[PDB]
Image (tube, helix red, strand yellow):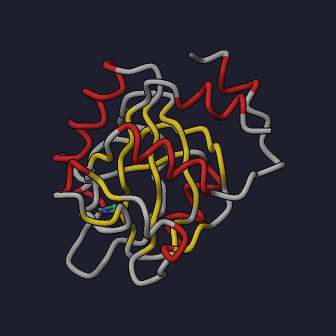
Amino acid sequence: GTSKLKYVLQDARFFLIKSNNHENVSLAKAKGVWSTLPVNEKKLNLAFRSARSVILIFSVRESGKFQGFARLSSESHHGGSPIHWVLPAGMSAKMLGGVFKIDWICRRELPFTKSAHLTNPWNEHKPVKIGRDGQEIELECGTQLCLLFPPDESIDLYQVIHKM
Ligand SMILES: CNC(=O)[C@H]1CCNC1
């Protein structure tokens, strides 16, 4: 069903996450973590305290798809086991911010061809696929985008609801 998902998404905030490679998204799906540059780390920490759910919607650059979405379960923290992210040419692990814990809500892909009717008011009403890493997605657009993904029957949202 979609009812528990709608409950998790009620009054949530949404952020577009752009990764240069599939390796980082696969790591995030396996380990339940994300890290971003400090400018975006600060925004996500503010958002985490402000709303009952903060949703990250992931897209690998040049893939033509989103790769899933997850909910922040923590603010960023430093000093864990170093995650072996593949950073793009010119980027070093020192340039990253802290580590956020995330709970995946959907690990399934959605092609951009399916979201062409959704525009993001916070990015000049451009199609929601368009945006820099960290672009916030307005509530209605983000809710409808998450509802377009195929259901991920491997995930039980009962375990996310209790953290809210
Ligand atoms: C693992 N973290 C990333 O790949 C971030 C870095 C900047 N945009 C995506």
Q: How many labels does the image show?
A: 0
Q: Quadrant of ligand 1?
A: bottom left
Quadrant in the picture for residue 28? bottom right
Taking the spot 23% from the left edge, 58% from the top edge, the residue there is 125
- Left of 126 or right of it: where is 164? right
**Left or right, 83 with reference to 41:** right
Relative side of 95 to 99, left or right: left
Q: Which of the pair 98/135 is nearer the observer?
A: 135
Residue drawn at point x = 43 percent, y = 46 percent: 142
Q: Position of residue 32 (x, y in %)?
A: 59, 45
Q: In this view, does 109 lie above or below 136?
A: below
Q: Quadrant of residue 127?
A: bottom left
**Placement of the N terminus among the 4 image quadrants:** top right
Foreground pick, 148 / 92: 148
> As drawn, which residue projects farthest toward the front?
117
Query: Front-most of 116 and 13?
Result: 116
Q: In this view, does 55 lie above or below 30?
A: above
At 39% from the left and 41% from the top, the residue drawn is 14
In the displayed structure, 83 sits above or below 143; it is: below
Q: Position of residue 97 (x, y in %)?
A: 27, 46
Residue at figure coordinates x 66%, y 34% from the top left: 5
x, y percent for residue 86: 42, 72
Q: Where is residue 159 in the image (x, y as percent from the top left)?
A: 73, 25
